Image (cartoon, rainbow, N blue to C red; front, side, top):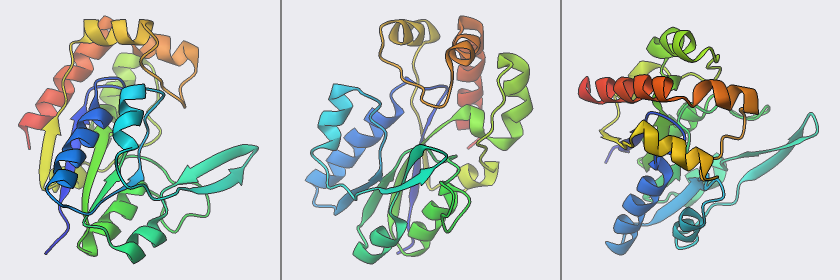
Length: 209
């Protein structure tokens, strides 16, 4: 049986992609599926941290790079253990230096070729075809990109939707964490106008699948 990819697609950070993925994963766990978390970003949400702690977890690999402790999915251990389903946040991620592959999507393709199912999350901004539209709207450069075909050839795609106004409240209320984005950049990104634009992109993306 070929590995099947399910992508939880969202307009932006904070729309609930990871939580949706972890709830989907619990349904599978309950039905007896050997589920393993490969890489999951809970981003300080206690409810998401509580879902993750009910799932088997594969320790990450830590490296040091320019003072920073970088974490990657332990691909080699996952291939060896051969779980039935691996959970992998952030489909557009560019891997830590010294990784076998440049991109986390390649890590995923490798699991999938080994017959391992994969659940993943991605924000719409990372799609290659949309890089310039996103930069034109937000004024922020998207540096981690994803070839559109990686998402197009996904077995399953689910849109995780949230109103922009509500996402702005979440950001205000300390519920949205965006690690590799400085304050000036977050302020430039998370506006009503920009989030409305990105929500339409996510929907147009989901409809074209």
